[PDB]
Image (cartoon, coloured by chain):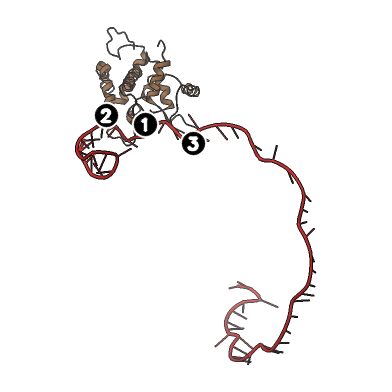
Chain colours: A brown, B red
Amino acid sequence: YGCSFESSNPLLAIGSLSARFGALYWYQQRYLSDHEAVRDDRALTKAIGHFTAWPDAFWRELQQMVDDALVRQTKPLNHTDFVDVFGSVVADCRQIPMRNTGQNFILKNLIGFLTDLVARHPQCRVANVGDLLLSAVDAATLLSTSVEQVRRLHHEGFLPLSIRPASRNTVSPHRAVFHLRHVVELRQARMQSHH
RNA sequence: CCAAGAAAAGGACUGGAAGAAAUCAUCCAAGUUGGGGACUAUUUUCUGCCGUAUAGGCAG
């Protein structure tokens, strides 16, 4: 009904109401997968405790699935889709309606993590994590901008395309084609703002 | 409920004999195909011991 908080240590304890609503919606689909039992009070009541160690737990949830994915590998990683390892955790960032990083704190932590992941895995002769392919709609989300802007950014040569398409065809938004390390670096280099 | 209704064309057979297509001949003269250009990339093949040895055999 209102916020009214002070000494807001948890990442769920600050902000405008729309964000506070979005954070709960996200928590629910992701951890309350059990079918509705109209436990309208009890089901959501737990979300606050959950977030109290967030700055240090979210990363472990992401780390766990890097390893479980790795041991099930069937192709060299540089032809593997980003989605096969992280399971659309990126798309879920779109459920909070705000676009910028300083307000959408879920996206802010996911990017933090991916930047570190790339940093500890530099390029060498054998491919490794960080060379995964992103689709056009994924870069748009990580770069905090609409899709048409990515097409314009490609056209000017600020980033490379890795898969050669056939002639008399087009690459659709859903096709996986940019390397992760290329997107992370470009964003640090030329996409920052006061937000 | 048809110019309606029914229906065994069968049996036999020696085309033969003979022949010279031939003589002649000039396809020639001329002619500008040319101008430009990346097979390597997100490659997988490293590190050692024995053996005179770029031979031959081996662990990871």
The chain identifier of the residue carrying mark 1 reads: A
Residue position for label 1 = A78
Q: Position of residue A188 (x, y in %)?
A: 39, 16
Q: Is residue A111 visible?
A: yes
Residue at the extreme top: A6
Residue position for label 3 = A166
In the image, taking residue A156 as reference, residue A4 lies left or right, namely left
The secondary element bearing badge 2 is classed as helix
Residue depicted at 27% across the width and 19% down the height:
A47
Question: In the rendering, which numbered label is found on residue A67?
Answer: 2
Q: Residues within 10 Å of mark 1 (few under 14, many from 20)?
A: some
The chain identifier of the residue carrying mark 2 reads: A
Question: In the rendering, which numbered label is found on residue A185?
Answer: none
Query: Tag 2 or tag 3, which sits nearer the N-term?
Result: 2
The secondary element bearing badge 1 is classed as helix
Residue A112 position (above or below residue B45): above
Q: Amino acid at mark 3?
A: Ala
